[PDB]
Image (spheres, coloured by chain):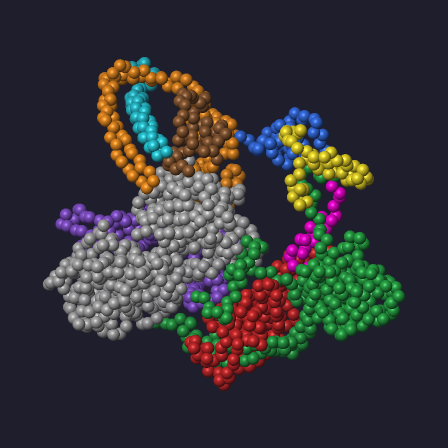
Amino acid sequence: MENWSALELLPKVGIPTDFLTHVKTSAGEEMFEALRIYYGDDPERYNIH
Amino acid sequence: MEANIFCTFDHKLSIADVGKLTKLVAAVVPIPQRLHLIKHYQLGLHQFVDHTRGYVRLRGLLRNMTLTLMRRVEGNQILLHVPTHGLLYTVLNTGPVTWEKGDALCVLPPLFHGPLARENLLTLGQWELVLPWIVPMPLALEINQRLLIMGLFSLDRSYEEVKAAVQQLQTITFRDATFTIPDPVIDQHLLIDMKTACLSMSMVANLASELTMTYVRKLALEDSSMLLVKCQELLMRLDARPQHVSPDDEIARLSALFVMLRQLDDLIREQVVFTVCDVSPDNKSATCIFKG
Amino acid sequence: GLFSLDRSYEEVKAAVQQLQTITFRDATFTIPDPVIDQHLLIDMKTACLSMSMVANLASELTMTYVRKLALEDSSMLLVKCQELLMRLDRERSVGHVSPDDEIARLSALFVMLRQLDDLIREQVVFTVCDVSPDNKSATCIFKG
Amino acid sequence: FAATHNPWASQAGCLSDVLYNTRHRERLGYNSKFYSPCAQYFNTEEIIA
Amino acid sequence: METHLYSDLAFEARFADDEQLPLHLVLDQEVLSNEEAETLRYVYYRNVDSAGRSTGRAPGGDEDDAPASDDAEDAVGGDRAFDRERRTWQRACFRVLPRPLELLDYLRQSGLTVTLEKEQRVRMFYAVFTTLGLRCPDNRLSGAQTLHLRLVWPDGSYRDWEFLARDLLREEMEAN
Amino acid sequence: LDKILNVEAMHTVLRALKNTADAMERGLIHSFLQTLLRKAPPYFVVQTL
Amino acid sequence: HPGFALTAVRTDTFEVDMLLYSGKSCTSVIINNPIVTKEERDISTTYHVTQNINTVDMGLGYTSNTCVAYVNRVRTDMGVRVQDLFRVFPMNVYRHDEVDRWIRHAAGVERPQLLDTETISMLTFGSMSERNAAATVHGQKAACELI
Amino acid sequence: QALTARFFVPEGLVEFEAQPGALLIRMETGCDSPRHLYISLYLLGIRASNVSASTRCLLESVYTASAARAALQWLDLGPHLLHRRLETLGCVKTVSLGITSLLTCVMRGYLVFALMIPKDMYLTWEETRGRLQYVYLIIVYDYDGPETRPGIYVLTSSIAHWQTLVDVARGKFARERCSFVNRRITRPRQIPLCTGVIQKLGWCLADDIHTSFLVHKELKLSVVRLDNFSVELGDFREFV
Amino acid sequence: TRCLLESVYTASAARAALQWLDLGPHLLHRRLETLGCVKTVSLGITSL
Amino acid sequence: DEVARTDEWKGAGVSRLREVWDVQHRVRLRVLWYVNSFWRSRELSYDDHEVELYRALDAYRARIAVEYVLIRAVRDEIYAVLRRDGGALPQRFACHVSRNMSWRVVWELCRHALALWMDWADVRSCIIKALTPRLSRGAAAAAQRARRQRERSAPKPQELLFGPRNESGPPAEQTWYADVVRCVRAQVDLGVEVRAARCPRTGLWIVRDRRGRLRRWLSQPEVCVLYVTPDLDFYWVLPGGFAVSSRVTLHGLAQRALRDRFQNFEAVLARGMHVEAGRQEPETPRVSGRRLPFD
C-alpha cells in the first residue's frame, strides 16, 4: 500500500486534464494500477508518524 | 459515565502496523469489562475464539459484551469511544456484506466466506486482532434461525442422513453474497434454547382457538391461489357454523397466543445495535444511530 | 380478520357487530372492518393465514420434537408439556416423515412466525408527563 | 434466444468441445504445434479467465 | 425419577400405534462400574419373537436369512443390512444419579409413597434410571419372549445381556 | 510541522468552499434548464401552431 | 393455427441528443443568498447549503421550442420475446392441482420451490419476479404484450 | 439533565412513602371517579407473597387509610393479572404533606438521590460483586395454590443483554414455570398470560449499595438501598 | 518434501523430463552430467 | 377442577420390587412397578407354553453359537490345509533360522499351542475384531473402490503428462489383530492389535506394535502366534517364521445372526458432539458426582 497521505499533504503541480471516458468510470472499470477513493473527508491525512 | 476507554499496546508499534490501525479508525470493536483502562489482549475476539467449541457459545459471549467505536491512534495509545444511546455516529463496514438504506443492523461472530483467505489485522506475536460482523437484520435473523433449525433437526439422527441436510442448511445466500456457519456444534445453551422453543410451541399448539385451527382448511375450501396451494402442498401429508363463538374468550385466547409467539420470536431476533441513514456508495462506511 | 370467512351466520354477525366497538376512558369508537365487499384483502389474508399456519404446524410438530428432545436429560417441564399434548390429542381425536419435507416444515413454521413480527410487537415511541384542558397539546419524552 | 443452434457443438460434453478445447484435448493425443483454427472458440478455461 | 413418568406417558401415547408396554428398570454397582456409569451416553433395547426374530424385520422372513457370502465386494449386504440392523434397535430415555443413595429413602423424598411388601433396604453406590419396552403383537403376551439391553459409551464400546420375559413378569403378571 | 498541518486545514476549507460555490452555480443552471425543458413543447406541435 | 390471430405491442427506448431554442429574457429567475445550516456528528460535521430559486413564465403562448435531434443508438433489442404473465400475475393458479402443474411444466415456466420471506414478499407486495439473464449482447429485452 | 415530573396523590397513601427516596407506580382502575391511583413499591409488599409475615404485619398496620384500602381492593380485584394494570413512573425525591400531597418524580436523570428497596424484596443471582450492575423490577406469578397471589422482587445483576437474563431467570424460576403449565392443564377454562414480567430501570455503581433501617410512626423496617443511582424506564417485557 | 516438490513442479515440461528419466533401461548414472551453479533469471515462455 | 396425571401418579406411588438375572447369570438388576401405570388398565393376557420356551432357548443357543462355530471353522481350515500341504510350511515372517536344532520339540510345542489356544477361545479373540470393521457401511464402499483401483491399466503417457498427478495407491502399513499363546506357562493373549509391513529386501512380513517398536515373540521357542488380515485372510505362525495360509470360511453362518451379534455401532448426535461429520469432539459431557452438578 502506497503512502497516499504523502500525496495529499505535499504540494502539487497544477495540470488541467480530461480522461477520454468519465473520471468515475475510469476508476470503477479498473484502468489504473492502484486506486484510493473516499467520499466526504477522510481524516487520515491529518495523522502523521 | 465512562464515556471514554483507553487501551495501551505492550508491544512495539512498527510504522506499518500503526498505519494499518490508522485506516481502521471509526470501526467497531467490543470490550468486555467497560473499565476505563484496558490492556491490548481484550481488544477483539481473539482471546475467546475457539473452533473446537460451539459457535453458539461464541454467539452468546459476543451478544453479552459491550460495543465501542474506534478513534485515531498515537504512540502505544489507542483510544476507544463508547456510544451513547440515541446519538448519531459514523461506522465502517468490517465484513463484506452489502449495506442498504433504512434497515437495521445486528452484531454477530465472524463467518466463513468464499475465498477463506481472511485478511489478518495487527498480528502482534501470537495475538491477533479480529473484528465482529455487523450485519443487516434479514441475514442475521436468517442465520440465527437456521442455526436453531440445525440444532432441532440434527438431534437423534445418524451422520449419514445429517450429512445432506447440513450441506443444504449451512450455506446462506444474501443479497448476491454467500456465507457459511463456521462450527454449528450442539451445546448446552442450544439445548436450553430448544427446551424453551418446545415449551412455547406446545403452549401455542394447545391454547390456540378453534377458528385459528380450522381457518386455513375453510379458506382452502373457499379460495385457490398460489400461496394457498403452497400451504396445502406443505400440509398435504397431514390433511360449518362454529358451535361456539365468544368474542371475549377469543380476545383473551389470542392475547395468550401473542405472548407465546412473542416469546418464541425472542429466541431468534438478536438485539438491534444500529439503525442506518443513507450509506456511502462504496459500501465501506455509513452513518448510523446507536441503540442499547 | 379470523371471522371474515364465516360472516353469513347470525351469531357471527352479532359477534362481529359487538367486536366493532371499543370503549376507553369516556371515549367510544367503531373500528372499521378489514373486510370490504364481502371479500378479504390480500394483506389481511396473508397475515391471518400465516398465524393460522404457524399454529397448525406447531400442533403436529410439537409431539415429535418433545419426544426427540426428551431423549436427553428429561425434566418436569417436559413431562407436564407432554401431558398437556396428550390431553389435547385425547379431546381432538373423537372423530414417519421425509427429512427434506421435515426441514421444509420447520422452515415454513419459522418463516410464517417471522413475518408476524411486524404487527405483534407494539413498540412504544412516546411517554408523557403533562396535561392541560389544552388536551390537543401535550409534552412528552421521545422513545423507541 | 434459442437454447443453441448446434447441439453437437455447443454443450460442455459434446463433440466440438471435447475435440477442440485445448485443455480437454490434452487428455488425448495432441501435437501442440498445429494451430487449430477454432482453438480460440473453445478454450472455455481461457475465455473464463 | 422423572424418566419413568415421562416414558410411561410416551408409551401410553405410542401403544395405540405400535403396541409396546413399558417396563421400568434401575441398575446399580452389580451392573456397571462407576466410571462407565458416570459417562453413560446411550441405552438401547430390542424384543425377540419366541422362534427368534426382531421387531423391525418382516416377521415371515428376510434376505438376511441367507448364508454369508464371504466375497470381496459386499461382505454382508453392507448398506441395506446395516440400515436394517440400526432400524431394529430402539432408544429409550435415561437418567443417572452419580451420588450414592438408597431406593426407599430417595423415593420417599420424592413424591412417591412407596409401601413395599417389606421395607427391604438396598444401598446403591450409584444409580441409573431407565425404562424399556417389550412388545405383544396383540393383548396376548408370551413369556418365552427375550429382551435385549444395550449400553453405549462415547468411544464405541458396548455391553449387552438378555432377559427372559418369564423372569421379569414371574409374579406381577401372575396376579393379573 | 504544526504550521504545515494548519495550512493544510485552511486549504481544505478553501477547497471545500470553492468547490461548493461551483456546485451551487452548476445546480442553479441545471435547475433553470430543467424548468425550461418542462415548459417547451416538441417541434411538430409548435410548427403546426 | 390455433384459430385466433394475435397483434403484439412493443416498447423501444432510444438515447438522443435534444436541442432547444429559447427567446431572450423569455423567463426570469428570482434567487437568494444561499443559506447554510450546521449538522455535527461524532467524527465529522456536515454543512447543508440551499438556494431556493423560483421561476416565472415571462411570455404568452410558447417561448421555448425543442426538437429531438440525433439517434445515438437503441437500447432495446427490438426482439419479440414474450412477456410472461406468470411473472406479471404470479398469484393466480388453476383450480385443479395436477392440471396446473402440467400447464406450468409444459409452458416452460417454473413455480417457486420453498416458502421464504422473499417468496412471500414477491407474492404479496411484488418484487423482481425474474433475475437478470446470464448475458446480453442484444440490449435490454423488448417487453412484448399480446392482445 | 434530570427530567422532572409532578403528581398529586391523597394523604392516605403517603405516610410511609413520605421518606424522600421512594419508587412510585401508577395503577389503572375500573371505577370511574378514581380513574388512576398512585401506589409505591412498599404498598405492593402487603400483597406480595415474598414478603415475610412480620413485615406484612407492619405494612398492614401502617396503610389503614380508607383510600389505601380501596386501592388494595382494586388491586386484588384484578383476575390473575397485574402488569396489565400497573405502570412504572420512576424514582421520587420531594414531598409536601397535607390533605392532598404534592411530590415530584424523575423519569430520566441522575441528580440525596438514593433509591430505596425493602429487604424482603431484594435478591441477586450472583454473590460476586461485578463493578457495573443493572437493576430490574420483576413480577412472578405463583400457580401451585388455589388462586394466584403474585410474587414481587427487585434484583441486581451484571447482565445487560435481555435473552441471557431471561435464560438465567428461567434457570432459577423453573418451579414457577412448571406451576404455570400445571395451572394451564388443571383449569382449562382459565388462560394465564405469563409466568413473569421483566422491566428495566437501572444504572448504578456496585460499590454504592447500602443496607439500612427505616422508621415511620416509631415503626421499624429493614431496607436495602441504592445510593448513586440513575433511572431509565423501559417496557414491560413478558417472559416464559 | 516429495509431495511439496511434486505439487510445485506440476508444469507441463517438468513431467516430460520425469518420464524420460525412467522410461529408459539405463540407470541415472549414465544419463546425467553436472554443470555447476546457476545465478540469474530472465523469465518468459523460454527463460535465460 | 382436575389434577394432572403427574400428581395422582406421584401420590399413588409404587408397591412391588423384584430382582431379575440375565440369561447367562452375568448381571442382576431390579424392576419397579407403578400401581397407576396404564399397563394395569389394559388387562392383557399372558402364557408361556413350553414349546415356545424350548424354541426360544434353542434359538438363544444358536445366537451364542455364532463365534464358537467360527473358531471351529478356523480349526477345520487349519487342519484341512495342513493335510493338503502334507506337512510343508514355507517361511513367511522375517527371522533367521538355525539348522542344528531339535525341530521335533518345537513341532510338539506347536501342537501344544494349538491345543491350548482352542481351549481358551472367546468372543474376545482376534477374528471377531477382524470382522468388526468388515460389517460396517464403509467397508463395502472401500472394497469396491479398492477392487476398481487395483484392476486398472497402466496410465498412458498422455494421462501422466497432463492433468492429475499419479493417483495415490495403497500404503504398506497394514493393520492386523492377533492372538498369541505361550506354552512355557499355560496362558494366552487374545485381544492384541499389531502393525504390519512387508520387508523391502525379501517379501516376508515384519510385525511391530502401534508404538513403532519391533516385536520380539517370533524368536521365542515357547510361543505360537495367530494373525488375521482386515480382508479376512488367515495366518498361523510357529517359531522360525514358518506359517500356514488359509482364508476364514465364514460362510457357515447366516447373515442375520452374524449381524445381530456384533457390529461397529454407528452413533447419533447428542449434547456436545459436532454436527459436521468427523470433527474433533469437545470435552466429554460426563454428568458427574465427583463435583457439584452444574445447573
In the rendered structure, the answer to whether residue E19 lies left or right of residue C92 reads: right
Does residue B93 appear in this view? Answer: no
Q: Colour of chain J?
A: green
Q: Position of residue H215 (x, y in %)?
A: 19, 69
Image chain in cyan: F
Q: Position of residue B182 (x, y in %)?
A: 51, 50
Q: Provide the letter of the chain coloured red.
A: E
Q: The chain coloured purple carries which letter?
A: C
**Residue range (magenta):** J134-155
The chain that appears blue in the image is D
Left or right, G46 with respect to C100, comes to: left
Q: Nearer the viewer, residue H169 or B9?
A: B9
Q: Residue at x 59, y 70 (%)?
A: E149
Q: Extreme right residue here?
A: J100
Q: Residue at x 84, y 60 (%)?
A: J90
The residue sitting at the left extreme is H99
Q: Colour of chain G?
A: orange
Q: Residue at x 22, y 66 (%)?
A: H43
